[PDB]
Length: 615
Ligand SMILES: Nc1nc2c(ncn2[C@@H]2O[C@H](COP(=O)(O)OP(=O)(O)OP(=O)(O)O)[C@@H](O)[C@H]2O)c(=O)[nH]1
Ligand SMILES: O=C(O)C(=O)CS(=O)(=O)O
Ligand SMILES: [Mg+2]
Ligand SMILES: [Mn+2]
Image (tube, rainbow, N blue to C red; front, top):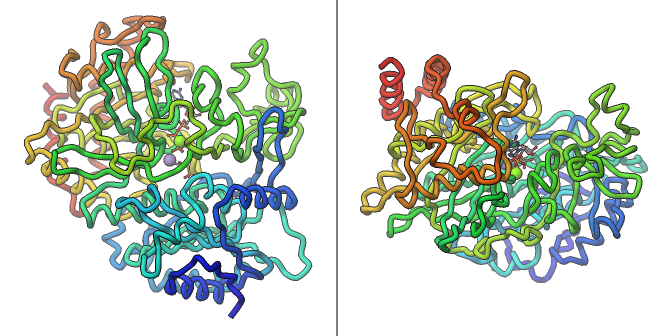
């Protein structure tokens, strides 16, 4: 067989045998084992610069940073090409794409046979969770993309240290990735190799992940969505814990009390911005710190609390919209040591994306850019055609340690206790600014039935309302109704300790006015909603009972420093009977689709809401 170039520190015979088998299948020219060092990162970045995949940014404006632009067919997740291949179709469920596992294996085998001819296979060892901690899991991703390798260095704990934990007998999650663009002898490569045919396949019984044809984000960084949500959610269902599409933040009030909250918003619907928000005027003495911005692993303890950890090591964040007013901690995070994907290039070798003009002299657009497709871009082109200089799903990749608001426990494997959960989708209508659920069951109902308008984070038509239970529609690794039951059963376990359960809130930052602009300013002003949640956690916040739960009155929030009237508050908090009647019929359609194993508690809760609407 091909020389694996196995390092001496790899002591795991089963791992080596699996690599050998994948090398025999994929047939790369050579094999390279990533050690995770800073020096290797620099070498791989230089290799990407030579291929044209990276441009090195101006070191005076953006130190040790790089810009990649991708093929326009490969800019986002492809949900229709993503599969849960469980043994039984009912363990994938109606929210997932299923194929009989032997039939998927026969489909993928000819695609992966020889997929890496002409390329290097990079062996990318990584830990999700702190290295060697009781809650961490180790994965090995084989990829023919050095872009994957350098992004995994930032997003995970990557490299040779993993093999001390694996030892001789440790188990690992097996991940195989190819851009699906094998190269014949002497063939010239493209700057962003990919395939218009794509598959992202999970076999839960074996924890195998196979990815074909995409080099982009969640399709190709397999530790993130594929393992730490899809495979992990399955493991959690079996072992009594949760893997959730949630930020985790700490918030300290002026009395020095610190609380932690976990919030599930759908893809490109506000988590990263919320997870490091800066308290605005009126909140002297408050602080907000980031534990994670995207994935949370959560389990209950004997003390009746829920403990959350962030299994990632960095942020893979949406760039457009980011500036010193919307997310200054993010702006400071990406000052250097960052990879940017599909943003624009300034004449001086810096990066630009829509939204940055809010910090510019005269708040004006740059005179000239190279947009993410390599085309000349100007304010005149943008005015006449609406051309975006940065793709709407353009991303930065940056280490968590760049974040000035990073929580000191961000990598503590003991986790943080969650005092409240927040769920919220992108809804132009219907859903009020913030609602507290009256019980755990009603909160699970909130989360199970939430809707959200599609975004550029996956391909397809944006702006369409769909059901997105728990913000996990693209990421649930088993039947969604069983996952609802898991959340209900978790609540009963917590309550049996005698504890008070974490409260569950619904939020909506995204109500629109008649011109399609947002009625609520959002971003740092979301602190004013968070502060009410903290008041409620302490039993000092007032609220009014309405159809869907308990909501603050105008006087229950701090408006110091924000010009937002009681009339504007009434608009975004009023419960509209007609809109909620329509919404509950969309819940009924979801419950028909999810009939199999649907918890009866959900239909019971729906009936109670219907009574309150008809009262
Ligand atoms: N109007 C408004 N826009 C927001 C708000 N928060 C975030 N956004 C915008 O929504 C987009 C997505 O925000 P993110 O915070 O990156 O979303 P995310 O949930 O982290 O998305 P993923 O990383 O894909 O899971 C960006 O363009 C933000 O500028 C908000 O409170 N109000
Ligand atoms: O789409 C999301 O929810 C993301 O966090 C980005 S990706 O990792 O799926 O590309
Ligand atoms: Mg994010
Ligand atoms: Mn996400």
